Length: 150
Length: 152
Image (cartoon, rainbow over all chains, first blue to last red; front, side):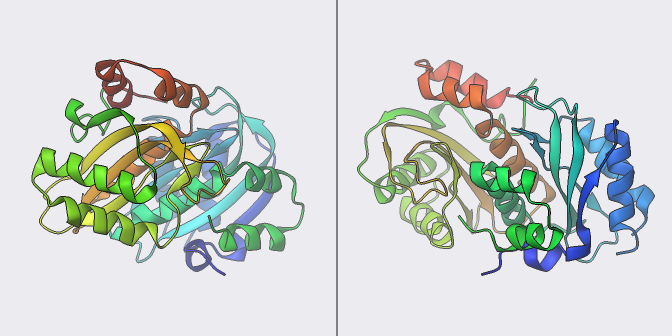
């Protein structure tokens, strides 16, 4: 059955093979993914400035970049897998290749904490994480992301 | 380098060596911790933690969990750390029993800070070295500083 991500992480927001070197480039591209779904500038600059406060890496090559976007009516998420891991100042010093981006509206709701909780839990699951690293099919990645349960 | 836990996780809410047979018993102990701190009725804390837990385990895997709930009347978040003497089954996603818990209670009215507090807790518990430190550190004062000054 479906988790909270099913509502907010559409198929077209699951992107793979992104081959970049800079963290900035990853956030620029995340901005393009979310664009008008809101402006790319707002998304990229918010996410990047937050990244500057402290890495959003959870360890083991995954990260949850997130931010609040004025004007957004509902939360939005995206998954990005990089072709090569990049330095991300992660707590364990390992480079990051798997990112779930989360944008939330300005007005907080209880669901926002629960959505981020679900994302952190999914990415913490060792076997799910391995599967996110290797699965070649976008439809299958999307199913895995949006149907994962503890 | 204080983090968002510093303001909501006082030393008296760092509890170690707790022996419990079950999730029910640890949630009851969390109720007493928060009642002792804030006044919120222990049974309301326990009931609300369970109300959330029934929707899905709050285990993150690797023996750690973030049980959480919302509290009517609460003006700001409350957090506590509990280390169990022995790990207990917790229906965790990886099936590993749980011995390290950071409880979080938040006001019924959400604010942007709540997500960020959760994010910080999840990140620190997700760090391998930190889990080992939390598993082994004998000094409560030190555990308290580790938790409240943790940075990625």
